[PDB]
């Protein structure tokens, strides 16, 4: 049997659920019949990105319609889609192209999870759960619901639930202390930077095996820089609800996982509008999309030397900004150190 705590057992089962991986692929409109879970190849995904990269260039520069049609055929031939009785849409709309780049960011993590799931599973003396836990290379511990850590984190969750996101409530079901192998060592040079904060990062539950084993990642070189608001970096929020929206939960599937990572921000390059940042302006360490609402700076506390903006959402004073909420982006995988993983239950307001 399993030697882990129950909630950790439930967590592992959840992140390695094969049926959720399929559901995710069906939502992305992949043809499960022509492209099974076991067909996902890392190379396949890279090629797909290059295609999206090239087609995006064509739509932007007025390339031949022939070109856009050929690229679309190559894309769909590489990643079989099932559109039902609908005619397959061409990759001629920049918004549909973005959606497709998002799907590949997700397919990269799903591929990792499946690989691990069918990897080294040969032992009778180890429960299947324990074996999979070990594949994660991450030490996971349950945080006691009554310690200071738990209390602070619960406050952070309750106080930063944004106004426009009142389509649901949030209940913290469990809090885990996580420590990915070698991550603390990688992040060490950044302890030197000032302005290190405890920020949020939401994702689908099907991404967690990739997140835990590989850590948070930046899109590969093939990915169009345009496929992202502020370029190819790692995104965070100080409003729990802004992130929570990326868990992609529903009344039918209410449980979501969310991360709390310590991020070395330093001098932030503050922006009010989307910008495809290719390189940072000497002297800056991160980007900060300014929003109209943000936690109350007066309430900002600290936990282990890291700033926690658990303040109640207040208006920020900036009027000329595209964003409703703050957005933080780092461009180096080493500028983040994952700390906590929260199991959330979305209580969706009813009929």
Image (tube, rainbow, N blue to C red):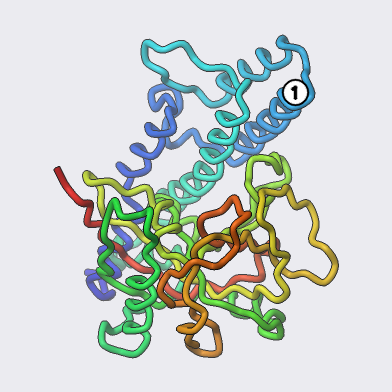
Judge whether 307 appears above or below 83 on screen: below
Nearest the eye: 73 or 281? 281
> Quadrant location of the N terminus?
bottom left
Secondary element at image label 1: helix
Q: Quadrant of residue 223?
A: top right
Residue situated furthest left in the rendering: 351
Residue at (56% x, 21% y) in the render = 76
Horizontally, residue 171 falls left or right of residue 262, namely left
Dot 1 alpha-carbon crowd within 10 angstroms: few under 14, some 14 to 19, many 20 or more: some
Total labels drawn: 1
Q: Is residue 180 visible?
A: no
> x and y percent of residue 115 in the render?
47, 48
| Residue 77 screen position, x and y as percent | 57, 19
Task: Give the residue displayed 45% in from the left and 63% down from the top.
Answer: 135
Q: Quadrant of residue 203?
A: bottom left
**Residue 5 coordinates in the image, percent (x, y):** 25, 75
As drawn, the residue found furthest toward the right would be: 282
Residue 287 position by quadrant: bottom right
User: Which residue is label 1 attached to?
Assistant: 58
Q: Is residue 285 left or right of residue 102?
A: right
Q: Relative to 47, say whether 251 is above or below.
A: below
The C terminus - image quarter: top left
Q: Residue at x 42, y 36 (%)?
A: 37
144 vs 18, nearest the viewer: 144
Q: Is residue 40 visible?
A: yes
Percent x, y of residue 14? 30, 56
């Amino acid at each position: 049997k399993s030697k882990l705590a129950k909630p950790i057992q439930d967590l592992i089962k959840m992140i390695f659920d094969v049926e959720s991986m399929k559901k995710a692929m069906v939502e992305f409109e992949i043809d499960l019949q022509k492209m099974p879970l076991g067909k996902l190849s890392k190379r396949q995904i890279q090629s797909a990105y290059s295609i999206l990269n090239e087609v995006q260039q064509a739509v932007s520069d007025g390339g031949s319609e022939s070109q856009i049609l050929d690229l679309s055929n190559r894309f769909y031939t590489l990643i079989p889609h099932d559109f039902g009785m609908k005619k397959p849409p061409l990759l001629s709309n920049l918004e549909y192209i973005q959606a497709k780049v998002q799907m590949l960011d997700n397919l990269l993590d799903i591929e990792v999870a499946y690989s691990l799931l069918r990897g080294g599973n040969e032992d009778g003396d180890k429960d299947p759960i324990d074996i999979n836990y070990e594949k994660l290379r991450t030490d996971i511990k349950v945080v006691d619901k009554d310690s200071e850590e738990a209390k602070i984190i619960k406050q952070y969750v309750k106080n930063t639930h944004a106004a426009t996101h009142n389509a649901y409530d949030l209940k913290v079901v469990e809090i885990f202390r996580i420590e990915r192998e070698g991550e603390s060592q990688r992040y060490k040079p950044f302890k030197q930077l000032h302005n290190r904060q405890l920020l949020w990062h939401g994702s689908r539950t099907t991404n967690f095996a990739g997140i835990l084993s590989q850590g948070l990642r930046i899109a590969p070189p093939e990915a169009p820089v345009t496929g992202y608001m502020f370029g190819k970096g790692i995104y965070f929020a100080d409003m729990v609800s802004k992130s929570a929206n990326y868990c992609h939960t529903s009344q039918a599937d209410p449980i979501g996982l969310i991360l709390l990572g310590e991020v070395a921000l330093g001098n932030m390059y503050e922006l009010k509008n989307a910008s495809h940042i290719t390189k940072l302006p000497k002297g800056k360490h991160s980007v900060k999309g300014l929003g109209k609402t943000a936690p109350d700076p007066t309430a900002t506390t600290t936990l282990d030397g890291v700033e926690v903006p658990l303040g109640n959402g207040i208006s920020t004073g900036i009027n000329d900004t595209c964003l409703l909420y703050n957005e933080y982006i780092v461009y180096d995988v080493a500028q983040v150190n994952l700390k906590y993983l929260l199991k959330l239950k979305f209580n969706y307001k009813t009929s």
